[PDB]
Amino acid sequence: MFLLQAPLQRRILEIGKKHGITELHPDVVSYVSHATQQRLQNLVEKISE
Amino acid sequence: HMVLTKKKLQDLVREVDPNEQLDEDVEEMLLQIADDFIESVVTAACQLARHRKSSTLEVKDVQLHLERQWNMWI
Image (cartoon, rainbow over all chains, first blue to last red; front, top):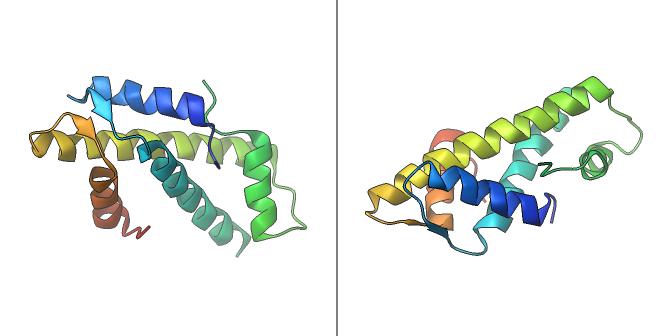
């Protein structure tokens, strides 16, 4: 996984508590990791351009 | 706690341009951006979920926000 699975999991779970969320589907972690990799991938590509 | 490593970041950078070591400050900035991204996205998603009258965070929620506020299609 691009991002660190354990702390990511914990941090997502953590942000949810503050926002009416009690649980989170499993692969949501991976999905967020993928999205974050895209966010950063585009910026880097742009920066190198 | 750290969710992304300097190593993994650098692999990403390398993937875009194999010969290009990024300045540490830029590395930190990007690590900071990933943090804001996770924060805002997950936060906005939880809202969508809560709206579904739900309490379990699901891809559906994150995807909906990404597509709408980031025009990211994954």
